Structures are given as structure tokens and as C-alpha cells.
Image 1 (cartoon, rainbow, N blue to C red):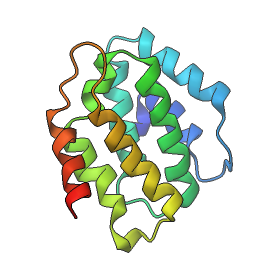
Image 2: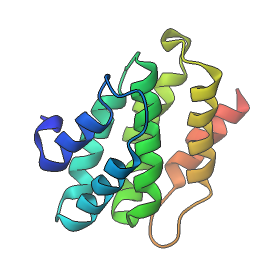
Image 3: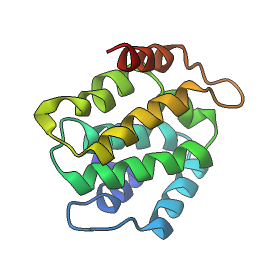
Image 4: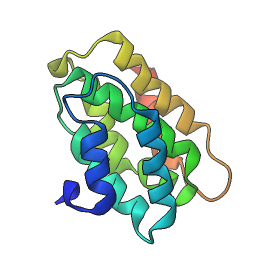
Length: 141
């Protein structure tokens, strides 16, 4: 279970349906944990993947994306490499752009924006070949 792991639980709570705003103090604490534990990055992405997947909640997705954008720029490629994997962007993030989830243009453009930004590559390893194509498709159609 994703929300079971130490850092997994902090994520479940930081993006809980209840909260109506971003607890940036908490998100930071989350990143620091991601950077301390041995498998924090992997375990974190499993929880984020959960929270995101086929979710119809506005704020949960809004908060989760904000939480993602945080880790992306506060944790090395050890994290960035798992978020740009096709298993995440194509089978989770981009799914939300489907009409079925009727999410607002606000959140929609934010999704495209991550794709476009992550497609720009990050410093160091991180292979963005996949998300690079996931972006191109959103542009073509």
C-alpha cells in the first residue's frame, strides 16, 4: 500500500481531500524526507501516483500537482527520473486531460505545462525521451 510508507503517509495527508490550500511548510518537510531516506523517491512516487490516478477531486489534484512541482525542483534526478517515466505521465497525468474528469482549464494547462517543462530536460542524468514524446502528442492533437 502506498499511503502506508513513512513518506507515503505524509503525502496522503498533505493532499487530503479536507485541506483547501497548499501547506508549503509540509511539502518542504516532505521533500527533505525524500532526500534523507534510501528509497524515499520511489516510495513517494508510488503514493503520488495513487493520489493522482483517475481522481475526480479538484483540490486533491491541484494540491498534488503543487506537491509534485516541489519535489521536482528540490530532489535530484533520483526523483525526476521516476516522474518522467511513461508509466507515470502517460498512464496517470495525461489521463486527467480526458473530458471524463471535466477538470478546469486551470488545472488542464498546468498539466500541459509540466509536460512542456519536464520535456525541456533537467540537469544531470534524467532521460526525458518519453515525456518528450508525450508532449509532442498533446501538441499535435
